Length: 220
Image (cartoon, rainbow, N blue to C red; front, side):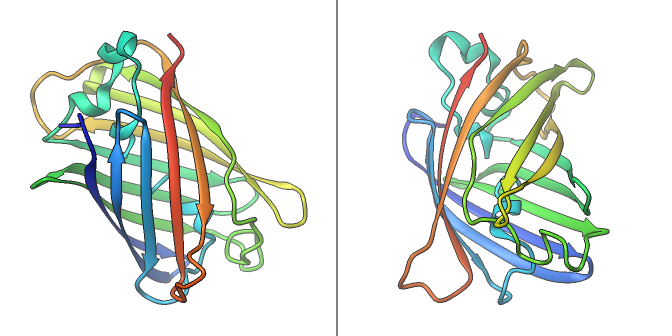
């Protein structure tokens, strides 16, 4: 399923502090390189929150798992039936996002369909006030087997640099559970070294985000 380039489609319906928006993304992924290339468009106009705050929500099955760690790749093992991915994201001293996504193959395309709900954000906070830098730091995504639910428990803290020079933390709590009933690979503890680079197409006038992502599994 992931031997070569795979087309990707991402759909997100969001509601933050009552502000409703929709984001659509398209591109491709190459697990062999652990690379993702995607463009996202806010199809409802201006995005009410900073693009960087939606990166983690907007397909870890594209991570490059070295061959000696392939028995720890839950993400691809759950395919093509896919997995449900849910998170709660708390922005320090501000609101939180609650998301529920379904990641699976629809025809030849890997599709990530998400629903996001944001509550308790400060009107003039770093989020609703768009005070975050348009960039992204590298982070380690810690994965643990969740034997019980035959899935995984994932945790990590995102560091969003603020335009004033400070840092806006976003604690992520995520759970992944297979959509299929068959067995999947339950990994030993490990992490995904994840890198993201954000850019803009100067010719594009719609509110958008061009994203390049590099991810390699490690820890074993």
